Amino acid sequence: DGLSNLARRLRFAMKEGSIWLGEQRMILLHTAALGALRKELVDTLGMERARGLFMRMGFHSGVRDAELAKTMRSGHSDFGMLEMGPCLHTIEGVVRVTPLTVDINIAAGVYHGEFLWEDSFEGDVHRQMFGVAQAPVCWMQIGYATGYTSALMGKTILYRELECVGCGHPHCRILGKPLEQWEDGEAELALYQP
Amino acid sequence: DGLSNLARRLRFAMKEGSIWLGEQRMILLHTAALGALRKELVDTLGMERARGLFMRMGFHSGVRDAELAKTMRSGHSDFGMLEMGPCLHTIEGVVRVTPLTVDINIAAGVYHGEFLWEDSFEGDVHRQMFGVAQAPVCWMQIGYATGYTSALMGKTILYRELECVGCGHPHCRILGKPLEQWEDGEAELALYQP
Ligand SMILES: Cc1cc(C)cc(O)c1
Ligand SMILES: Cc1cc(C)cc(O)c1
Ligand SMILES: [Zn+2]
Ligand SMILES: [Zn+2]
Image (tube, rainbow over all chains, first blue to last red):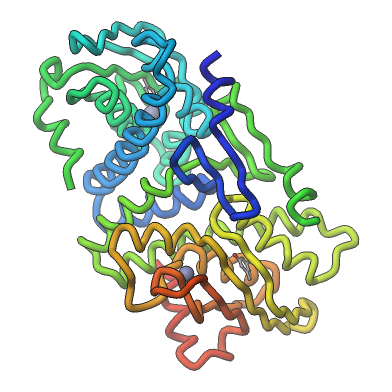
């Protein structure tokens, strides 16, 4: 339902060498090319700084997709709106998202959400350039979730991967909740600032 | 046409969370997300070093697309081969490309090429992140032209932007020729190196 409905917002305007998702102009980019940039940033600026750059990039993506979701608001419950994030992330070929348990009420500022990530392009590309890492690696993907749901909730919602293929697990798994639920919350919120 | 023949190689598996162009996995990325990262890379690394990173990302992309083009080469001429570059760049929503004059013989190592760029995304995004620039800004677009043509020729063929929207012009225009056939060429080459 969501996928096939949000997918109609994706448009290819070749007369103008352009691709549009709702109101945001998009490009098709090779994962290997974005992987090479990551290798460069990590090799020179260091892993933890490269991780902030990517999380932040993903954040900005997430916020934009939330604004598109807001326009198609009417007729959707709070879960329906939230769902659109996982849907656009999947359409964008970033990851296959399966929403498991989602507790949301925007009016009350309620949010607790856990999702499954399959075929994460990011974990799958960090490994090709860096082998297995001893910490979750889908930086840009976590950034997106955080930005989207934060835009949607109108308060800081932070996400973390509980499991990542970049660490050598069968899947990535993530959890998102208010900044008051996270033990290292202020340290996590810091990463999203230039 | 090039765009129709090359469209058959773009596979959207929305029920997979993936996108493939030939045998390269792609993502759809918000140009505004790329702009954000560009701003942080300039602000902290400086214009020139940021530029190197984007040109090299473009280069990786153009090289992968030339591999795709070399697959479909049954009865296509050298120009037909070359023309797949500009086509792919368009399909990817990067720019609207119009070849102006192009002399190419792959066997003979000859290449002289001139191209019109309309609605270049990169010049658009730069302008919104930094204002008008005091030199050509379509870095990844250029890297791409270089990388693709070079892989197709088996010979280093560099491009430069002769005119560009990011600088105040109504469009971008570019020149591609042999490496050493450039004055500071040996210096342009240095930017395609980590
Ligand atoms: C907005 C969003 C939310 C979740 C849980 C995953 C994703 O890929 C995107
Ligand atoms: C390989 C290539 C060549 C030209 C002229 C434009 C472009 O966007 C890519
Ligand atoms: Zn992961
Ligand atoms: Zn330009």
